[PDB]
Amino acid sequence: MNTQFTAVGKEFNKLERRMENLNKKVDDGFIDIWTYNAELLVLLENERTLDFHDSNVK
Amino acid sequence: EIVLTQSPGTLSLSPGERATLSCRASQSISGYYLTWYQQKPGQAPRLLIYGASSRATGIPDRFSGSGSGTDFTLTISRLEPEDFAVYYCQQYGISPVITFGGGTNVEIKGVQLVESGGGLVQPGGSLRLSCAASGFTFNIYDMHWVRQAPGKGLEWVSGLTTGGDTSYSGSVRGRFSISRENAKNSLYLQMNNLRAGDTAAYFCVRGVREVGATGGDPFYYAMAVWGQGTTVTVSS
Amino acid sequence: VSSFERFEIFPKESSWPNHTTTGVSASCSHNGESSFYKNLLWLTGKNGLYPNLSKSYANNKEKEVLVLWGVHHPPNIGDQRALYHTENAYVSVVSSHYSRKFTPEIAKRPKVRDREGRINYYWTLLEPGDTIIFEANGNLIAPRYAFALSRGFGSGIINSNA
Ligand SMILES: *[C@@H]1O[C@H](CO)[C@@H](O)[C@H](O)[C@H]1NC(C)=O
Ligand SMILES: *[C@@H]1O[C@H](CO)[C@@H](O)[C@H](O)[C@H]1NC(C)=O
Image (tube, each protein chain N blue to C red):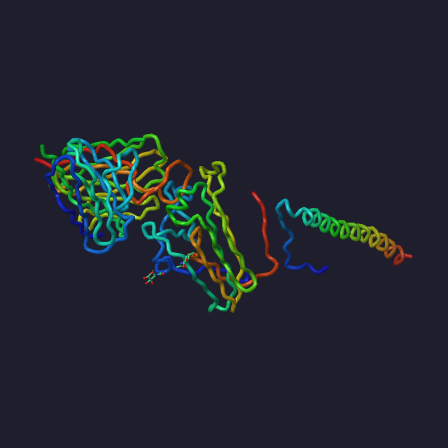
């Protein structure tokens, strides 16, 4: 990771709904991507970790 | 604020006649700045004219004036014996200080406030007055306490804008003290160190719509409305 | 924020002799006593005496500047004639990048915080080197104070009750 000195939030009127549903779509997109990658990563890395142990004992 | 000088303090004239009165000061002083009154002795003041031209509500058309700068003027188209009265000259300083011409008798030849507490005290002593408000928004207007000896030129004791900029006279200041309440709809004047100069009648007075609110209430830089006043005296 | 502060671009004293300044209203209040916003001004005539204005500023501080102003929309006309003495509205708040004018009318509205009237608020950033001009026939809210600043990066905004 690189964690910026970040500011997440925005907020808008109701004549910007292009941008509202955008920024929703944007953020939810990114959120889901990190979520999916990280969940697979914990699964796989733990699988290979068990295999790493298994290998060393064998 | 500046010394005024009425012209004349008393006159004697006949029916079916005009009447020219000239209230003029030291300096030249901008002309939507004065307002003009009448009083029957026994009665409170009544308002007539403002800004050297223009006319108040509920009216004939006869009292009408002109003039600018140093010399402000109210003329009169017709005289009548119901007009038997002392007319006054009240101006809002830029140093926010009302100044007062000393009354002008015409002799003809052949909503509301309520004051509280007028009466006696000992000289050098201490006493308070109040006023209370009826039927409006005491929020808005710039208020004034005023004095008047019997059959004399007036004097202005104090006034205050609704933000907090006081104006007193340098002689009166400190011995009196004002304080205001809008939620309660009332005004207060705690007074101490009192001598015979205060031996006179006083009035609570509602002036100026500051800049803004809802209403059917325009503004001048004259008064809005007066109270019935009350007497105060030191004596022993 | 990287830098942020408050200064007095146009001191209330000596900015506007030729318009009476000190008028306020009673909704903008402090402990049950009337007021108006610190950073800004009303302007009105010298006993019903409106001249029309041209004023300006540009940066000497060499930092970036943040400026606010307003445009008067009375709920009735008798104010508009009485204060400013024109039914004409024409204002022109101008810069190199930004520029905009204003010519509003009376437009009646309901009581909102015991007010029908409105003042629409308008603002911009202003950099070093660039000049701003105000021109007007009244119906203004002016800067008394202005916000000096540098930029910042990465900080932001929260809604929270905790
Ligand atoms: C006000 O107008 C007069 C015109 O004679 C001028 O001399 C004076 O400098 C003006 N003041 C301002 C602040 O514009
Ligand atoms: C005010 O605007 C009027 C509109 O025509 C113009 O004639 C006059 O010269 C302007 N005065 C000033 C002081 O800008």
